[PDB]
Amino acid sequence: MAVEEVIEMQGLSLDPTSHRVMAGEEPLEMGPTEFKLLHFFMTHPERVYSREQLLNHVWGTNVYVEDRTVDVHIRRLRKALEPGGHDRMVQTVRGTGYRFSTRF
DNA sequence: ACTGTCATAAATCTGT
DNA sequence: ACAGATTTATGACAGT
């Protein structure tokens, strides 16, 4: 089928059709760049991504900003998932980039 | 209201 | 153990 389908993993559920993020069946709220970065991470758990890979996928290939736009948006995404208990999935690889994980 | 940039603090790696 | 160089986290502000 071509209709989109909800992703539910480790108590966190994201619906691409409704643009709706919920943790433990209680909603969380975020902007659309934050949602797209979260959608990219939840479709790719257990892989390391540099700020360049995140820029080409989420912001766009021919779109231009500094690398440290990613750092501020990572803080905004963690701040958003923090009262939902799910900031700790979003992990940091020093000197390279970031990684998303179920636990470890 | 949402995203991009800068400033300062904390954290990491290597050399002595 | 401490200092210097490089990276990352956080808070405030501007532009559109």
Image (tube, coloured by chain):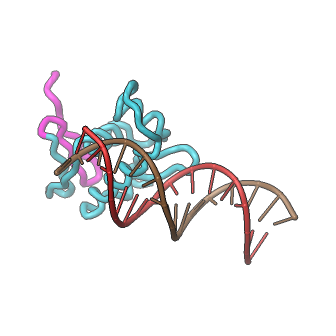
Chain colours: A cyan, B brown, C red
- Asked whether residue A56 is drawn in magenta, I would say no
Q: In the picture provided, is A28 more to the left or to the right than A93? A: left
- In the picture as drawn, the residue positioned furthest to the top comes out as A1
Q: In the picture provided, is B4 more to the left or to the right than A39? A: right
At 19% across and 55% down in the image, what residue appears?
A28
At 25% across and 54% down in the image, what residue appears?
A11
At 19% across and 57% down in the image, what residue appears?
A24
Q: Residue A104, image x and y in percent?
A: 45, 54
At 30% across and 61% down in the image, what residue appears?
A82
Quarter that holds the N terminus of chain A? top left
- Give the prevailing secondary structure in the magenta stretch: loop
Q: Residue A16, image x and y in percent?
A: 19, 37
The residue nearer to you, when weighing A67 against C16, is C16
- Asked whether residue A14 is drawn in magenta, I would say yes
Q: In the picture provided, is B11 more to the left or to the right than A1? A: right
Q: Residue A3, image x and y in percent?
A: 13, 26
Above or below residue A12? Residue A50 is: above
Question: Could you say which quadrant of the image residue A46 lies in?
Answer: top left
The residue nearer to you, when weighing A104 against C14, is C14
Question: Could you say which quadrant of the image residue A84 lies in?
Answer: bottom left
Q: Residue A29, image x and y in percent?
A: 19, 53
In this picture, which residue range is highlighted in magenta? A1-18
Question: Does the image show residue A49?
Answer: no
Please give the count of numbered marks on the rendered protein. Answer: 0
Above or below residue B2? Residue C11 is: below
Question: Does the image show residue A74?
Answer: yes
